[PDB]
Amino acid sequence: SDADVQKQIKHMMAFIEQEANEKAEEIDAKAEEEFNIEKGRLVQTQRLKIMEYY
Amino acid sequence: SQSQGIQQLLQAEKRAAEKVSEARKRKNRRLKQAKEEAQAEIEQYRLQREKEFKAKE
Amino acid sequence: SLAEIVKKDDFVLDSEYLVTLLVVVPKLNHNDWIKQYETLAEMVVPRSSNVLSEDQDSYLCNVTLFKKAVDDFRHKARENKFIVRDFQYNEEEMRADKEEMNRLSTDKK
Image (cartoon, rainbow over all chains, first blue to last red; front, side, top):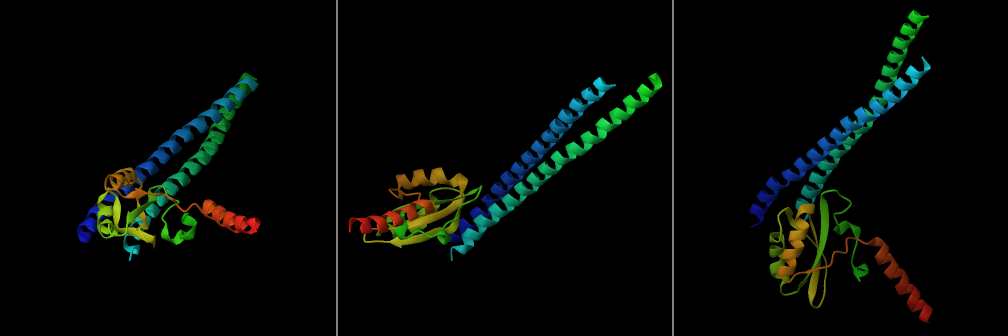
């Protein structure tokens, strides 16, 4: 029994590391979204104020 | 001893936490980058509007 | 009350993908449970069982495992007549029982 249980879990535990890597890739997708959102909000708000001044 | 199996659980969780933490660090760095790149682009727009305003003057 | 026996070193907690379950078994059936419990779900490590204590009828053990295992494990535990008692190191509750034990036994006197 015990040796087969050790081999089985040593295979299966890799899916936990894979799903954590996918969670990290989702946090990086949120990084790309929030970059574009923050840059858009800042640039458009100030571009309009600069335009109105001139 | 149970440390055989317990350290395999903790190893997968520590690896998982490292990947998630590294992505969270990148997320914070990207938010700072958005401020820096926005600050550059609004000044470039102001400089273009200034050159146009000086030409109209 | 679990306040008689529980200590932090027997538990794996405070984790995104890890859980501790707690299960009671009769003292004769414990000799089968020691192997059978690892069959109740996938995503269970070998030697995941830490015993907290025995008594005149039974044993209680912590089982350490990944989060995907737990609902299959608990349902198959109930199917095999093993009894769930998931006291996941409730430090506030063990301290409250100790405080009321010392207080009530003093205050009655």
